[PDB]
Length: 104
Figure 1 (cartoon, rainbow, N blue to C red):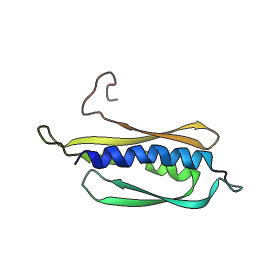
Figure 2 (spheres, one colour):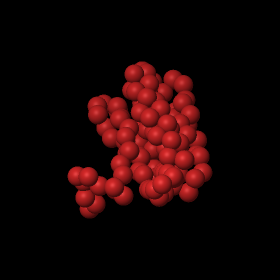
Figure 3 (tube, rainbow, N blue to C red):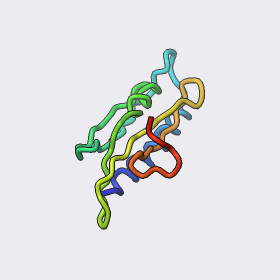
Figure 4 (cartoon, rainbow, N blue to C red):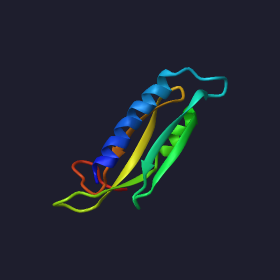
């Protein structure tokens, strides 16, 4: 359902936090790989292995689909951005229901 996205993206925001709080080996590679799992808009869970802090950027641009009862399946997009020296934050953008942003 929609909670798949809401859970996976939320935990990913925490994942980024872990990655961001974890020290990195020369190059920006991470001590220990983290498994992040996103379900694409077609409904297939893809498991990404974060071996470097920069792997967070791989997730930016990911598309999710949200199936909700009493509504419709909306397209959600995974967005990650830089906040510091190889430090990235995660959130989700929804262009299907725009309250302030307009598509360019």
